[PDB]
Image 1 (cartoon, rainbow, N blue to C red):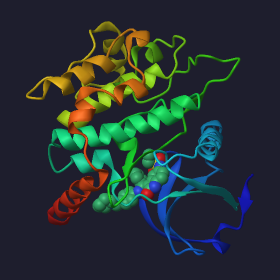
Image 2 (image 1 turned 120 degrees about the horizontal axis):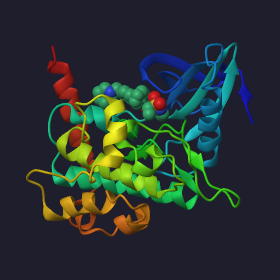
Image 3 (image 1 turned 180 degrees about the vertical axis):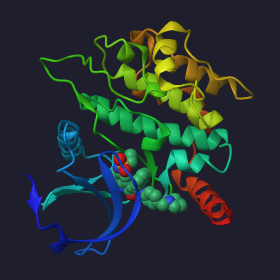
Image 4 (image 1 turned 45 degrees about the vertical axis):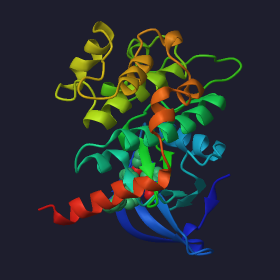
Length: 285
Ligand SMILES: CCS(=O)(=O)Nc1ccc2c(c1)[C@H](/C(=N/c1ccc(CN3CCCCC3)cc1)c1ccccc1)C(=O)N2
């Protein structure tokens, strides 16, 4: 269902970031005057990644959730592909970490929304496979959505597990690194690492070369959250970071976790985090 002549319907504005496969631009929907995001891919240089580009479009087109970046369509224009998506003016959760530590209400609120996205994807038999703070995007008013579906996996009636080596090493589950038959529980491990990332600012082993962590993650005991954090947050992380995937809770189960129930609050409060970043960035030299 590829479409054509995107500039009849959309206006391309300035670059707002680097994405997977290409650059992302702000844009305007000329029908509504709402702002959109436009990922532009040069298909002439897209030798090999073409399969992942195709997967991103396919997965996006099949999702309809408030917790997954909305998809407006894909348009061909010369050698370039325009992937038109929901605009999220708060940028990534990773960027919002830069000014300093989050508090546990912020951590819980963000994790809750990520969990609602994972619950949706997993119920659709989709596995994100690159869960990390960089792929968690916020609206300017604090709504949270999962993004970047280029390496997402799809389970079917004839394929009940995946085994592809994909993801970002520090966040990868041990069974993904070993390329065992795995499923949505791999996302739950990555969620645990992301919880540490949100709490401490960086995932475990962040100082090391990624090739080193590829042997450390299966070799070592799972990471734990160290430092002055509430018992339920430490236990949330521990529950996610089990070497045995079948012992990890589902996203649905984690939405009932004491840490989430006690600490998550209205998403609109996350606007404070966006304002904190704007202030920080404006002062930055
Ligand atoms: C996983 C990131 S991706 O592969 O570029 N895909 C993607 C999909 C949908 C999107 C986006 C990316 C954006 C997207 N939006 C965005 C990025 C950066 C800003 C600017 N910041 C915003 C926060 C206050 C200070 C300035 C505003 C919006 C984006 C682009 C590139 C990297 C991370 C986030 C968006 O609004 N919608």
